Length: 431
Ligand SMILES: [Ca+2]
Image 1 (cartoon, protein in one colour):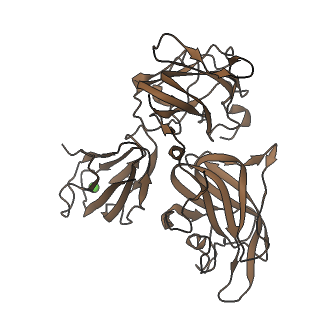
Image 2 (cartoon, helix red, strand yellow):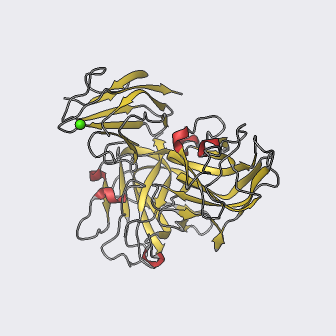
Image 3 (cartoon, rainbow, N blue to C red):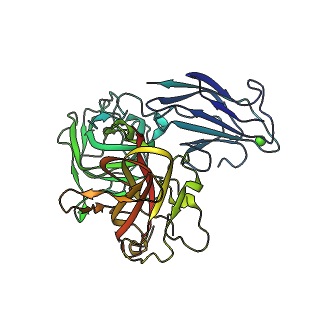
């Protein structure tokens, strides 16, 4: 048996037989488990796999393998970037085929103890490998890794200065973003000052479905710099739950040069705000159910925040308000303090094709049989929660804490395509 679990405060994870070459025909699962308020830190020391990772690979998973999100798939000679997870579970599945073996890998994991924290551009906590761009200037002197705030060596500049370029950051885990700070840059070679004067923001949970950030009807244009040295910070009028962030310059002085910091926090930094297992897969399929489901090709995993490639859809998605529900059995009683609601993906090129919930109700139960709705203190009736404005970008909706083993989300309003929904529940231990 290849597979292993790791619970000790500090440890080693490695390819079978390391430092010998790795065996053929392997499929191993390495899982690190941590109790709450503990951060998992994973650092690679050696990495060397056969090289598109079509043959041999190491997949890293934000939870359970093939259930929770894929953080990345790695092969070849380039060691994975360091990972810091606050999910409570980090998994690795190492796959090898019938021929060709290399040295493999060796890694170490550690278990260690206002949403306004810098996310790591200036600290280096955002690794070089997490930063990329649509293009870069042809001399190699204005690279994406030169886009860190207060960097002493130029900045990021694209191949050609237009409004179709972007600096991209992969935060690896779903993270709250609350502000962006930018600078221009002064040429060490020439003394010319270059800066971006305005930008747009584009975000995704998965790298494939993107949302340009709006203020009202229209795309938000953030005003940026007025010199090549001073930091201009913009606070987002509405904070964002995201993984991938793109900064997309719209205007500049003399040319696009960019230095950047991102500000925010973890979902769990708020009290009683642990993700209870839909995203990760610690809530099993058997614990997920609905009033109705699409008649063919339904798996309960379709309902899972972020990891699902589609969504829950009732049997007739153009339903009756308050009749359809998605239920989560948390497995044991909990204190529940919110949900994260998301739209349905798959099929995006057509705006009217996008299925998402715009308004909803919540009920909860310890019985599984007797249900109470969450109340509006004003109208003395079931509270109508705001849903999503987009099919990928999720929205956290907190409420006054409640004791529950079961939670139901009842779609009330929804996009023209009908009800489509992915979900997570937020809370902590019952007390
Ligand atoms: Ca092989």
